[PDB]
Image 1: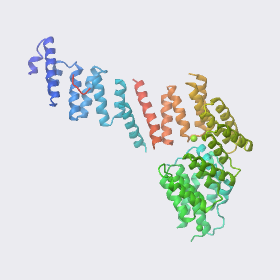
Image 2: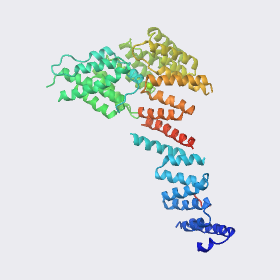
Image 3: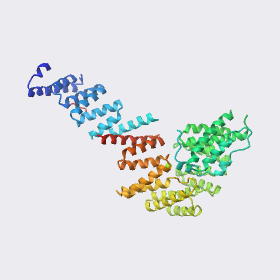
Image 4: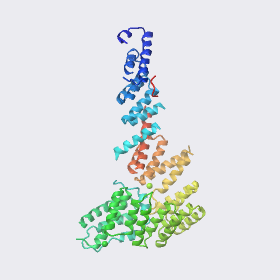
Length: 483
Length: 5
Ligand SMILES: [Cl-]
Ligand SMILES: [Mg+2]
């Protein structure tokens, strides 16, 4: 066509030509002769108000891989008709290819596995852009150290070296650790790292007391790395500790660091070595029992927990585990009786009603579970040191949130209040943050939710990605509602 | 969705 002469025909005749030129373009597109584009341009010169011509041009650029031209032409289609289905999906498809996942998800949302694919791509892009010196929550630290005999651990620092200038700092580190307080863990973490650095220097005139104190510093600085999820850092120090002076703790800790869902043969051989070094050490049996428990080997778990109990009968944790095993074995009555007998011995410890409340919740006795968590919270408030920390708040808030919308606005507000308090009392709890974030999102407090989801991701690899995913999904909802 | 109109 000479478009010169066509443009000077009538409006019926000029449009008629558009339908005719468009159709010629379509013939070529079907014949994989995309350079189609020329005929559509011709059509545009006669009818620039037709979004089909721009949308068709963009289908050609999809076919030849010009992703930037796809965006330009689908955009032109969409500026005429913002709800054009093919333009929206083509533009989302090209944006995904260019790595503009939020733009893709936006158009896919307006259009309505594709959404989910781009969400994942966005979460990994953001996780990779973003990404430890950060401890787990004080609640989780108190639980981890609950089995150990503080006095024994603090007194295991040797005061008799002629060269050791770090032992007093090491002693303060352990003192702080076993105070089981928010300040205690932060100070322990600081001073263990400092003691280890001093020990590396000292090791380089050395004597055996200094070697054993170094092994002790290395052993705890190692488990702190494990707790921070720096597994290689942990293994390096634990191995150094073993190379200096083998101890049951260093074997327990190295086993935890190298634990393997596939083969648990190595885990159990470390524990045999720990047993050999000291067959009269309660935490060895307790931790091995924990692993048999996790592997659902209840007979062997019971044996080990009974051994831990028989070596340190003043520690509440072996009793609790034994009661939990009864419940898992299919014996609630006997479990409840064991918890009650344990509550008689340890009437001030919140560990007993907190673990029992978890069993009640599993049974669906939510009202009794909440009463147990109420008691646990009061017992916890009265103690100087952390026992169960924010566990009861999270426990009760989770029940109340699920009961509220299964809206009971009083239970839902109560849950918010509980999780808000939990977040303030234990700022490094990702559990508390994510819990609160989901409720904020239900209330359409999107900005608040996003901040909580993002903090949780800082705090939490698959966990970091899950939190990042919640945050990125919420940012898209925010963008949609903004327009 | 891959077809011209
Ligand atoms: Cl030695
Ligand atoms: Mg926690």
